Amino acid sequence: SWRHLVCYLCFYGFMAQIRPGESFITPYLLGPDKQFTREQVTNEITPVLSYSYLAVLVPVFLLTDYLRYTPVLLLQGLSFVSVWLLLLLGHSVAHMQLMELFYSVTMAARIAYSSYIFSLVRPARYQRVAGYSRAAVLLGVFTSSVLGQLLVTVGRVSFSTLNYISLAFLTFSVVLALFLKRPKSVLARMLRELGDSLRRPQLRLWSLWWVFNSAGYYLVVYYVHILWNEVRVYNWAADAASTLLGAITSFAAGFVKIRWARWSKLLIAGVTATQAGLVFLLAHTRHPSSIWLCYAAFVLFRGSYQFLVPIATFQIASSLSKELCALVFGVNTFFATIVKTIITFIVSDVRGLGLPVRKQFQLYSVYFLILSIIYFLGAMLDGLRH
Ligand SMILES: CN(Cc1cnc2nc(N)nc(N)c2n1)c1ccc(C(=O)N[C@@H](CCC(=O)O)C(=O)O)cc1
């Protein structure tokens, strides 16, 4: 385990996210292999995934820490394999509903890897291993996107062949996850430990940052895709560049050392203000010069969030007394997706404050603005008390 414990963990994190046929699921559904109407792929496939992400997250984060994270990784891998198998068969609508349910299972179990890395190493190099793991995962996502687009656009393969390749890669990822090691009123004690951990000043700040900034980033990304498709070839290039910059920034965050608990609220406020500025710049671009300045901006935005994705996790592991690193990650992810759903309902739904995409992004930038003057006014409040 001297050389094949963190290196192997990063390698598995890289290989588990290689699904070259991931981003091409919708065209495959709408393609000639499966005769699906535009209306169904969007009204019977996306809502089920959206709801099941909320539904299946709770059991996953409740049981991942007791299961010691190897069974949850195996479940995520087998669920990815079942997703692609169901994609290959795809007999009817219910098959694809089950596929989306399993995909939501995978997205819910994504937290098990981020807890496994911390439960696998001594509580001294949490930050370095967090940076390594996030760099590996984001590099895997970037490689998956680039491989899919290279095979489809500059290569010559069908969607079925791409899905076969993705299924083979997912089988290999399951094989890799098999060899991973397993670290060596229960609910009442669980919640008591969660509350006592939340009483700490370092877990609480980064948990709030997760719940809010992660929700903001997810909203911004999920609607940046739609905004770019609204106002084609370079879209995947921008996505891959953003993911690669995210991997680089996660590596840098793993390798950065600053005196935390003092320059931590200030760092969060600065990063959130930078992200707010980037989103404001992204929204305020209607001139023809909207293929260089905005794309890159979004890239930076993604990287910015990733620059705080391995630190926050690390700052949750360094401030946890029990083996509840998975519980806090799961609760934070669940609350972040709850906040994202609430924001979507309040800004995107017609019944609520229904606004178009432009004003939607004007709201998201302002949402980050309220999220960058709260942490700004949190680094001087505690400074005053000193
Ligand atoms: C939503 N989606 C891909 C996706 C695309 N089209 C689809 N189309 C259909 N019909 N169904 C789907 N389930 C579907 N899924 C996703 C979701 C999350 C990440 C993801 O992994 N996101 C993190 C990366 C970190 C990680 O790997 O967990 C991020 O920074 O955005 C990638 C693609």
Image (cartoon, grey):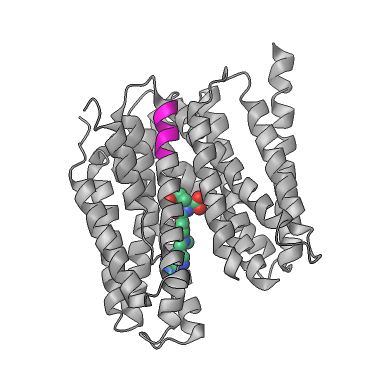
Q: Horizontal placement of 151 versus 349: left or right?
A: left
> Does residue 350 appear in the picture of this structure?
no
Tell me where residue 350 appears, x and y as whole percent.
Answer: 68, 72
State which quarter of the image contains the C terminus: top right
Q: Is residue 129 magenta?
A: yes
Residue at x 36%, y 21% (from the top left corner): 123
Q: Residue furthest top?
A: 386
- Is 92 inside the magenta-drawn segment? no
Query: Which percent across, then down, holds residue 74?
Result: 23, 50
Q: State the residue in front, 331 or 166.
A: 166
In the orientation shown, which residue stands out farthest toward the right? 287
19 to the left or right of 352:
left
Residue depicted at 46% across the width and 70% down the height: 154
In the image, residue 164 sits, relative to residue 372, either above or below, namely below
210 lies above or below 24 = above
Occupied quadrant, residue 340: bottom right
Mark count:
0
In the rendered view, tell whether residue 22 sits above or below residue 181: below
Q: Nearer the viewer, residue 12 or 107?
A: 12
Residue 78, by quadrant, is bottom left
Tell me the quarter of the image containing the N terminus. Answer: top left
Main SS of the magenta part reads: helix
Q: Is residue 364 left or right of residue 139?
A: right
Residue lying at 31% horizontally and 77% vertically, measured from the top left: 95
Q: Residue at x 50, y 84 (%)?
A: 38
Residue range of the region highlighted in magenta in the rendering: 127-134
Vertical relation: 198 (above or below) 72:
above
Q: Position of residue 45 (x, y in %)?
A: 44, 74
The image position of residue 9, as x and y in percent, is: 30, 38
